[PDB]
Image (cartoon, rainbow over all chains, first blue to last red):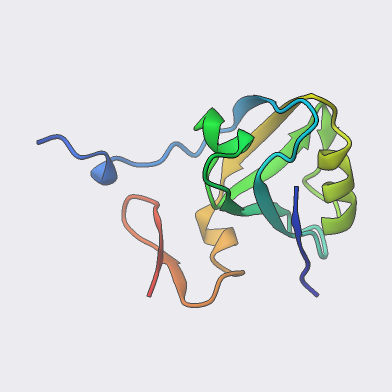
Amino acid sequence: NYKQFSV
Amino acid sequence: PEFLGEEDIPREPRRIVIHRGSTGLGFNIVGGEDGEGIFISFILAGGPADLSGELRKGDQILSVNGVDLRNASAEQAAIALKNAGQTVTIIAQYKPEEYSRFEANSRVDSSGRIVTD
C-alpha cells in the first residue's frame, strides 16, 4: 500500500 | 492579540483555481488505496499551490477540473493533476483525521490543526 507523488 | 491558531479550520469543500502554466503544482499527494482518498502531504514553498494560499496539508482532493478523485488511485490521481492543463480547478476538503493515518506520530488538536510529536 501507499504511494506518494509530486505534482 | 488575535491569533489565528485558536480558530477552527473550515471543514466544508472549497474551490481552488491554480494557474501554473507549464510548471509543477508544487505539492505532494498520498493515499489512493481502497478508496481511502487522495490527500495533500506537503506543499512546496514558493510553488503555485503555495502562492494560491488556499491549500494545506491534510486537504483531500475531491476533484480536479471536474474529474472526481474521491476514489482515485494515487497514480491516476497524479496523472490527472499533471495533465490538468495550465489552469487547474481543485475542489478540496480539509480532512485532518483521515490524513493523520498516513503521517507518523501525527494527530489533530482542538482547532483542527495537524500536530506531529
